[PDB]
Amino acid sequence: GFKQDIATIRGDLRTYAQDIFLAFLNKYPDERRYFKNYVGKSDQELKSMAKFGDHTEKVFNLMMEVADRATDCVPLASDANTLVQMKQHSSLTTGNFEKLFVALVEYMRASGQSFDSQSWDRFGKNLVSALSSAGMK
Ligand code: HEM
């Protein structure tokens, strides 16, 4: 289930973080505009860039923290608040987040693995609701 998925992802966080992030950019290529240093770079070039792996892992580490603190896939309002208030997220809308979770769920469904993909979808929906309430447009 969802708790196991957090363990699966954490077990190999660098790989999963990079592969899910690339799945997101692949499905929604216009989203790459938010990451100015990754424009025009192949996947292998990206993986050779210190901050690509480091920062992408940090994104997913926080995601796993928020996921683990949730109850029945309902995130803490304080965690939603953190995400809204981050300077790096100042121009984002909840739609950016829903796209990430759509790509993440698609990735899970296509993987050779028994992720609780329905739960990740529901967590994404609940997170979008919480982001909206905390002030994200
Ligand atoms: C629940 C989902 C998300 C979480 C937990 C999260 C978390 C984080 C964290 C921890 C950082 C700091 C990375 C660092 O400087 O090392 C970050 C940066 C950033 N995030 Fe988010 N993020 C999420 C979703 C998104 C989405 C959907 C977008 C846009 C499509 C986005 C855009 C950015 C950008 C542009 C940065 C700065 C990139 C950098 O300095 O390398 N994030 N995020």
Image: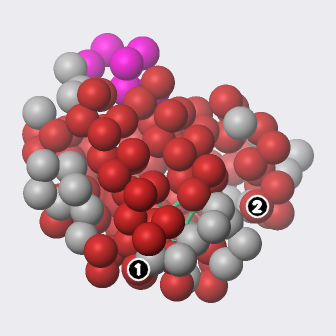
> Does ligand 1 reach within 8 Å of label 2's beta carbon?
yes
- Residue at the image point whose x is 34% and y is 52% from the top: 126
Can you give x and y, in whole percent of width and height, for residue 14 in the image? 41, 51
Left or right of 34, for residue 24: left
- Residue at the image point whose x is 20% and y is 49% from the top: 73
Residue that extends furthest to the right in the rendered view of this protein? 40
The quarter of the displayed image where residue 92 is located: bottom right
* 4 and 67: which is toward the camera: 67
- Is 80 situated above or below 72? below
**Residue 109 seen from this side:** yes
Disc 2 secondary structure class: helix
Point out the stretch of residues depicted in magenta.
107-113
Q: Residue at label 1?
A: 81
Can you give x and y, in whole percent of width and height, for residue 6 in the image? 20, 47
Dot 1 crowding, Cα within 10 Å, few <14, some 14–19, many 20+:
some
* 136 and 5: which is toward the camera: 136
- Is 7 situated above or below 23? below
Q: Quadrant of ligand 1?
A: bottom right
* Quadrant in the picture for the N terminus: top left
Q: Is residue 5 magenta?
A: no
- Which color scheme is applied? secondary structure
Q: Residue at label 2?
A: 34
